Amino acid sequence: LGQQQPAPPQQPY
């Protein structure tokens, strides 16, 4: 809560 959000998936090649 506060200033957090559902960030996108991280899959670096």
Image (tube, grey):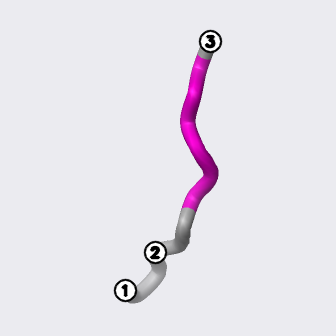
Residue at left 55%, top 36%? 10
Question: From the viewer's perspective, is residue 7 above or below residue 9?
Answer: below
Q: In this image, 2 relative to 13: left or right?
A: left
- Camera-near label (1 vs 3) is 3
Most distant residue in the top direction? 13
Residue at left 57%, top 27%? 11
Mark 1 lies on residue? 1
- Tag 3 near tag 2, CB within 8 Å: no
Which mark, residue 13? 3
Could you tell which of marks 1 and 3 lies nearer the N-terminus? 1
- Camera-near label (3 vs 2) is 3
Which amino acid type corresponds to the residue marked 1 in the rendered image? Answer: Leu
The quadrant the C terminus occupies is: top right
Mark 2 lies on residue? 4
Q: Secondary structure at mark 1?
A: loop
Within 10 angstroms of label 3, few (less than 14), some, or many (20 or more) residues? Answer: few
Which amino acid type corresponds to the residue marked 3 in the rendered image? Answer: Tyr
Question: From the viewer's perspective, is residue 2 above or below residue 11?
Answer: below
Within 10 angstroms of label 2, few (less than 14), some, or many (20 or more) residues? Answer: few
Residue 6 lies, in percent from the top left, at 54, 67
Which amino acid type corresponds to the residue marked 2 in the rendered image? Answer: Gln
Q: Secondary structure at mark 2?
A: loop
Q: Is residue 10 magenta?
A: yes
Q: CA distance from mark 2 to mark 1?
A: 6 Å
The span picked out in magenta is 7-12
Question: From the viewer's perspective, is residue 5 above or below residue 11?
Answer: below
Could you tell which of marks 3 and 2 lies nearer the N-terminus? 2
Q: Secondary structure at mark 3?
A: loop
Residue at left 37%, top 86%? 1
Most distant residue in the bottom direction? 2
Residue 8 lies, in percent from the top left, at 62, 52
Residue at left 59%, top 20%? 12
